[PDB]
């Protein structure tokens, strides 16, 4: 049989991947790139097999021919008799979060404020909110909407990167990988928590997972849910308990992608790997946990219960949903067809 070559984005993911590789007895090995797009390119070249992707990245990967293989499944809201691997996924809720103390800030007063985004091209952090903003403003100048932002992946000298902080050494400012302090769900939420930005574009889970003791991180350990509010599209503000009635969109879950000709093998290997290292896997937590990384969401989101089988052998467009695909396409007209590589 063949090894599966995972692609890790940045050095922290690479360290975790290397641990996984060792524990997997080399059934999984690691390639690494500086950005998700570069990992997608390694896979396109056949120099890596697979990685787990946010839905926007799935769009990029899908235009280039890669296919969804298995999806992140978090704990469900409702009892299900089904095994996690066979439980239909529920998408996650993309939200716009602000501080309660920032009174009078609403969806309709976002112009000229400071924003924190997971990364350019990601679902909750970018495609959904910027797509909505472009539409409502009738303008493609989304790079001039917020006074300053951290939007990892943007031009580092631009306003879209002005709030990004890079690493310990201040290096890698605005890179779209975990070195950047404010990268990803957790980074963008931290950007809001520290009042670097006025608004964070993340998902509902992020708020809950980093407040009220759920995170022991120095920056998060003392945060309280009641100190945050969600911005609803109708211009109201709601407590973070009201995400189901105050979100920007329902996002398709992050999912593993690969070339078609490697998909069945990547799938088989991952199903076995999670049986070993997944949530209440045979050798997790004793040996290694594939879905933990000290609330850093490395390789997979830390709230992943399992990678689940897809229904109906879906194309990337079916997986993302026609709604979301068209929204991405419309936004991309600002900055239809074909691989971006
Ligand atoms: C924003 O993001 C947040 C972070 O992810 C989300 O919060 C997380 O949400 C999950 C669940 O959705 C939450 O859940 C965990 O909770 C427990 C462990 O704490 C887990 O175990 C349970 O699973 C069972 C199945 O769903 C449930 O068991 C019961 O339900 C029945 C029926 O109601 C009851 O039985 C009865 O009692 C009533 C009384 O009259 C009677 O009707 C009946 O006759 C019946 O006999 C029992 O009371 C019992 O509750 C139980 O609900 C629970 O789900 C669960 O699966 C998860 O592990 C996480 O704790 C939570 N995380 C944090 C940090 O808070 C938000 O949900 C999300 N918001 C939105 C809107 O999406
Ligand atoms: C920014 O603004 C943009 C411009 O409006 C937004 O893009 C547009 O988004 C719309 C919503 O996605 C498109 O509308 C489409 O809606 C139709 C119906 O879709 C279905 O849902 C029903 C009900 O569940 C189902 O039956 C079905 O399975 C679909 O899921 C589309 O389809 C039609 O199909 C039916 C039969 O199924 C048929 O009767 C019709 O003839 C028709 O073919 C329809 O074709 C639409 O695409 C808009 O087209 C789209 N506009 C543009 C210009 O592209 C964008 O979302 C905004 N961005 C954000 C972030 O909000
Ligand atoms: C690495 O992968 C190999 C191949 O799938 C695994 O070995 C297989 O294990 C299953 C269960 O033991 C057996 O049915 C097969 O016969 C084995 N195949 C071969 C050729 O060895 C192995 O368990 C995996 N190891 C880890 C740690 O992931
Ligand atoms: O119309 C479509 O193409 C897809 C569609 C419509 C309504 C509800 C869900 C979905 N698709 C969908 C699928 Cl099939 C998987 C994961 C996430 C999503 Cl949003
Ligand atoms: Fe996402
Ligand atoms: Zn909704
Ligand atoms: Zn299909």
Image (cartoon, grey):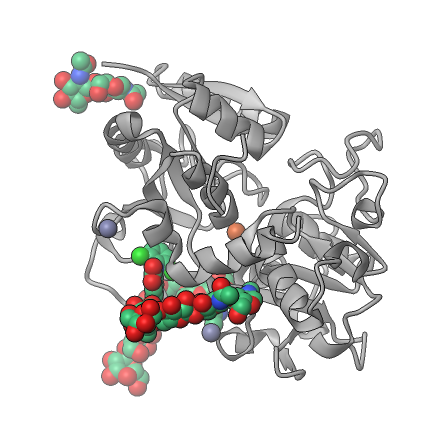
Q: Position of residue 75 (x, y in %)?
A: 37, 58
Residue 270 is left or right of residue 48, and the answer is: left
Q: Which residue is drawn at 61% across and 67% down?
A: 132
Q: Can residue 211 be seen in this view?
A: no
| Residue 51 in picture, x, y percent from top left | 44, 32
Q: Where does residue 272 sit, x and y in percent of width and height?
A: 26, 31
Quadrant of the image occupied by residue 136: bottom right
Q: Please tell me which residue is depicted at 62% across the width and 25% down the height of the picture.
A: 11
Quadrant of res 331? bottom right
Q: Quadrant of residue 297?
A: top right
Residue 275: tell me if it is visible.
yes
Name the foreground residue: 132 vs 212. Answer: 132
In percent of width and height, residue 229 lies at: 67, 74
Which one is nearer the viewer's eye here, 272 or 71? 71
Ligand 2 lies in which image quarter? bottom left
- Nearest the viewer among 86 and 322 is 322
Image position of 239 with respect to 57: above or below: below
Left or right: 330 in relation to 191: left
């Amino acid at each position: 049989y063949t090894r599966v070559v995972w692609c890790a984005v940045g050095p922290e993911e690479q360290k975790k991947c290397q641990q996984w590789s060792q524990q997997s007895g080399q059934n999984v090995t690691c390639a690494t790139a500086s950005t998700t797009d570069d990992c997608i390119v390694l896979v396109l070249k056949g120099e890596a097999d697979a990685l787990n992707l946010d839905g926007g990245y799935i769009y990029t990967a899908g235009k280039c021919g890669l296919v969804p293989v298995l999806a992140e499944n978090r704990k469900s809201s409702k009892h299900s008799s089904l095994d996690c691997v066979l439980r239909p996924t529920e998408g996650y809720l993309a939200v716009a979060v602000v501080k309660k103390a920032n009174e009078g800030l609403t969806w309709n007063s976002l112009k000229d404020k400071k924003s924190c985004h997971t990364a350019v091209d990601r679902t909750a952090g970018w495609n959904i909110p910027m797509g909505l903003i472009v539409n409502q403003t009738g303008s493609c100048a989304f790079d001039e909407f917020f006074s300053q932002s951290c939007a990892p992946g943007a031009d580092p000298k631009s306003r879209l990167c002005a709030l990004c902080a890079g690493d310990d050494q201040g290096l890698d400012k605005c890179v779209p990988n975990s070195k950047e302090k404010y990268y990803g769900y957790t980074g963008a939420f931290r950007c809001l928590a520290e009042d670097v930005g006025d608004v964070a574009f993340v998902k509902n889970d992020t708020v809950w997972e980093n407040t009220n003791g759920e995170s022991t991180a120095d920056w998060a350990k003392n945060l309280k849910r009641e100190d945050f509010r969600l911005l609803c599209l109708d211009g109201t503000r709601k407590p973070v308990t009201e995400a189901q009635s105050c979100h920007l969109a329902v996002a398709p879950n992050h999912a593993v992608v690969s070339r078609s000709d490697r998909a069945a093998h990547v799938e088989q290997v991952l199903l076995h790997q999670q049986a070993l290292f997944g949530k209440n896997g045979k050798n997790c937590p004793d040996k290694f946990c594939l879905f933990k990384s000290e609330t850093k969401n490395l390789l997979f989101n830390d709230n992943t219960e399992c990678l689940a089988k897809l229904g109906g052998r879906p194309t990337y467009e079916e997986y993302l949903g026609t709604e979301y695909v068209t929204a991405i396409a419309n936004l991309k007209k600002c900055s239809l067809e074909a691989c971006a590589f």
